[PDB]
Image (tube, rainbow, N blue to C red):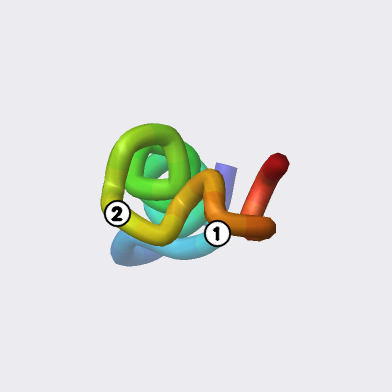
């Protein structure tokens, strides 16, 4: 796995948590 320096993996994994609680996350962002 050519996972250089925090690529897609780092992106998706982190994004997911924020959109979980992070304010503004359920306001149409996921609904």
Could you tell me which secondary element the residue under label 1 belongs to?
helix
3 vs 6, left or right, is right
Q: Could you tell me which residue is drawn at 71 percent across and 41 percent down?
A: 31
* Residue sticking out furthest to the front: 27
Q: Which mark is residue 8?
A: 1
- Using the numbered discs, state the Cα–Cα distance from disc 1 to disc 2 in whole angstroms: 23 Å
Residue at point 67% right, 58% down?
Answer: 28
Is residue 11 placed above or below 13 in the rendered structure? Answer: below
**Of the numbered discs in the image, which one, if any, rests on residue 17?**
none
Classify residue 28 as left or right of residue 10: right
Vertically, is 24 above or below 26? Answer: below
Horizontal relation, residue 14 to residue 13: left or right: left
Task: Look at 32% across and 36% down and name the residue there.
Answer: 21
What mark, if any, has residue 23 been given in the picture?
2
Q: Is residue 27 visible?
A: yes
- Camera-side residue: 18 or 27? 27
Q: Quadrant of residue 30?
A: top right
Q: Residue at x 46, y 52 (%)?
A: 25
Frontmost of labels 1 and 2 is 2
Sequence-earlier tag: 1 or 2? 1
Tag 2, which secondary structure?
loop
**Residue 24: which quarter of the image?**
bottom left
Asked whether the beta carbons under mark 1 and mark 2 sit within 8 Å of each other, the answer is no
Near mark 2 (Cα within 10 A), the count class, few <14, some 14-19 or many ≥20, is few
């Amino acid at each position: 796995t050519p996972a250089t320096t925090x690529s897609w993996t780092c992106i998706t994994a982190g994004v997911t948590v924020x959109a979980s609680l992070c304010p503004x996350t359920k306001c149409x962002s996921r609904c």
